Each structure stands twice: as C-alpha cells, then as structure tokens.
Length: 309
Length: 313
Ligand SMILES: [Cl-]
Ligand SMILES: [Cl-]
Ligand SMILES: [Cl-]
Ligand SMILES: [Cl-]
Ligand SMILES: [Cu+]
Ligand SMILES: [Cu+]
Image (cartoon, helix red, strand yellow):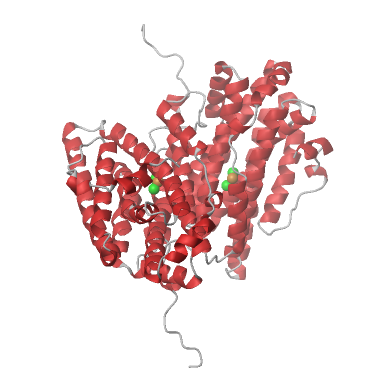
C-alpha cells in the first residue's frame, strides 16, 4: 500500500454525547472539536448570533410612554394581545422546538448553536415582558394572558407544530423549527412596523428589529440544515418531503389567516397583515430550497412598512 | 355558597407549552408571564447569569504564550488532555443535561434559565478550543481527542450520569444536573490553578474563573430546585432520595479518584487534586441541603491555590 495509515481517525470511531445518549452506544464519546470544524457555515453562524447578544434592558422603552398614551384603549389592548400571542410562540420555540433539534444535528457545533437559539428565543419572549412592565397596566397584562389561553384560533397554530417536535422524524421536526421564525410571527410583527411607520412606539420597534436580527438567522440556519439532509434522500423521498412542506405550509397559512382576521378585522389591518405574512411564507420556501407560488398582488407590502423591516 | 368561584384565573386552567408537549394536552397553553413571577429567586438567577454573559474571545490567551513555552511537552500534553476531558463533560451537560431539565421545571422562568445554562456550558466547552487555537499544535489537539475517546476511566464518569438525564425520574435527573457543575470538573480545574499560583498561564485561569462564575450558580440553582421538589415527598421517600444522593456521590468519587490517579500520578498532583475534588463534593451536598461528611484533612487546599479559586472574575 502506497498510503500507510498507522492510526484510525478518532472522529470516525466515536460519537458526540447526544448521539450516545439517544441513538448509538457502540463507541465511546468525543469532546466537541472547535479546532477542526466540519462545516465553516457553523462557525460563521455561531460568531454572528453570539456577537449579536442583547437584553431588552439595553433599550429605553420608557421613551415610548408619550406615543403609547396617544394610542386609544382598543389599540393598546390589540398590541398587548398581539405581543402576548408572540410570547406564546417564543415560549414554544425556546422550551420545545430549539432543544428538540440538538440531538438531530449534522455537526458538533450545530448542537451548541441550537442551545444559543433556545436561550435567545427565551430572551425574545422576555422582551415582551419588559415592554409590558414599562407601558401596560397589570389589568392589560392579565387580560392579554386570559385572551391567549381562550383564543382557539391562536392556539391552533402551535398545537399543529408541537407534535413534529415530540415525534421521531427529524426532517419534519426541522421543517416545524424553520416555520416558527420563517413564517408564524410575521403576522404579529406587521403591527409594530405599521405603528413605527406612522411614528408610534419607536423604542418598541428597536426591540422588534433586535428579535428579527436573530429570527432571520434561525430561519436561514434551519433551512440550510434541512437542505443538506433532504439532498441525501432518493428522488421519490425528496418528492414526498417537498409535498409534506407545501401541505404543512398550506395548513399553517389557513390557521394564520383565521387568527389574523380575528385579531385585525375590527382595525382594518387584516388584509395588509396577511399579505406581509404570505411574503414571508415565500421567503420561508426559498430558505428550504423551493420556489414561492405566491403572486405579487397577494404579497404586496407598503414601502414604509418594508422600510421598518 | 359563600366560597363559589365564578372567575377561574388563566394560570391554574392552562399549562406551559413544555407541559402540553410531554405531559398533558387536555388544557390550552399559557405564554410565559415575566410580569407576575411565582419565585423571585428565578428572576435573581436570570438577571445574574445574563449580566455575566462572556465569550472566550474577551480574554487575551495569546499573553500565556511565554509561560506556555516554559512548560515541557509532558506538561503541555497533560494540560491539553485535561482540558479536552473537561470539554467532553461540558458537551454532555450542554447537549443532554441542561436540555433535559427544561420539561421538569417547577416555574416558567426556570425553563428559560436552563436554556441559558445549555448555551453558557456550550460557551465553556468552546473556551478550551480558543485556548488550544492559541497555544497548541494541531498534533497536540488531535492526540488529546484520541486520548479522551480511548480513556475508559474518563468515559466511565459521563456514562454514569447520562442514564439519569434520559430516564423518567426528574429528581435523579436534577441530582445528576447539580453533580456536573458541583463536583465532576473540579479535579481538572485544580491543574490551571496549581500553575497560575506559580505565575504560569494566568490568562487561562481568567477563563477558568469566568467558567466557575457560571458553574457555582448552576450548582446552587439545581440544588435549590432539588430541595423544593424533595420537600413535596413523604418523609420515607425523602430518606430514600437522601440515600440515593450519598450512594451516587460515593460511586462518582470512586470513578473520579481512578481517573485523577491515572491523569496526575506521574506529575505528583493526584492526592492534592482529589482533596480539591472532595472539598467541592462537600459544597455539592451543602447546596442539596445536606451536611458534608468530609474532614478538614481530606479536603485541605494549599492557600495559594485557594486564592486562585476564590479570586473574582
Ligand atoms: Cl424563533
Ligand atoms: Cl429557532
Ligand atoms: Cl456545568
Ligand atoms: Cl448546569
Ligand atoms: Cu428562532
Ligand atoms: Cu453548568
């Protein structure tokens, strides 16, 4: 043999601890190796999300009190309800969705990045608390929580995704994980961007932009990992998974439209919020490596809302 | 009829998502409420660990190159091996241990705090990589990974804890979760502090102190939550769980002693490393609400080493 291999590489005869815990005990465990990185995209994402660390205490929400006080009681209630709705989706993602992805990682660094995502989506949920602490009465806060618990249209959306997280199909779990930052919160994010475009709650929209700076990377990353895994399947299994993605998005769009109509119809924002939602549904499909089937007309966003985005 | 409830509060007729996911789908989900906090200890812990956010890039490890170059290949190999061993334990805790705690939380905020722990223990593991990048050859780094995979005494320790994380007993899972930051890494932390007490690798010891600033809160918090849950058991079942804690710690001390003898005997550090380990075994039990059964002599630490430990980050 012209190539003498005296030792066998440690990496190919060991498993990460999470693999050992849940899947394969046939070999000993390897420590994470940050010196020999399998996918440089992992290091790029790790560096960006850790460099982007923030806490809601960094933003002076107190400065929004004047513009908040200009808003009628029904608008204040709409914002508190919408944001408590987004708090629920962040609680789902932080406590179930992100941590479920860790054991299904392609790489060692991916396990640590999803730990960062779980923590930072927790910070997202905590930030709404900070906004409420500054702007809302105890009565407004308590009412919003009651409204969320009793809103069947709102509950339907996380109830549809959670089963994919707790089941044993890692690709369907990954699609659910991408759908949360990629699609489900944009219907809600429409409201602060609408308000900011008209000069209301500027400091609140600064928190929303810090949340979105994280969520756009979360969607990209989960989509990137989905694409690497699905590419290794047969043409038939790739066709079945593409069908599953479109079928699940179709269902979630149906549930989102029902919820957004209920949330916004009284205010005249439902049509605009749904177009904003469908635009992001298109970007969600693109980040999974599929083509958007959505029309220019049904995805149209006002320039000044896009500007806030 | 004086006491009839006409209005049921949202909290007591809903569940957190993680409860809905793993335990009960009969009730609708509530969003986390940071405006009405059940346990003020959760907010204090959240505020401290988030305020204590750090990255290993923050510490100029390259300033250790002079003192690193003074150490012979045997000492450099010992440090790379020990630290890759600590990297393995941090990987176990970040990817399995902390994650496993979330669904067993007593409060909403506890679910988010364990997400923070999973991330920050990930940062701990990443910090050894930063030290290696700066100080070690590619040969030293690869050798240490091979050594960790093939070291049965090293492997035995995490292999003993992982089953508690993957099993359905949340109190045993919690004890394991406290044992990792409370006890299992201190045998390894002895080495950097031994060296920095003699003015070697001072910047490395700053990284270890930033890691310890997190791990002491992790141990306290998991111990605090253990004590709240064990208090809800019958006195009979409280006695059983106390016996399990002492039996598990006894077993883990056995495995740690074997590993530290194998790691250090050649460098004459084994006895002092084990004393340092048992000192922290004592602190671990105290944080679970039990008395340390260890003597002053069994737990003696040289004052110059204790000065490196107790020094604030
Ligand atoms: Cl998200
Ligand atoms: Cl995410
Ligand atoms: Cl730890
Ligand atoms: Cl921990
Ligand atoms: Cu996210
Ligand atoms: Cu820890």
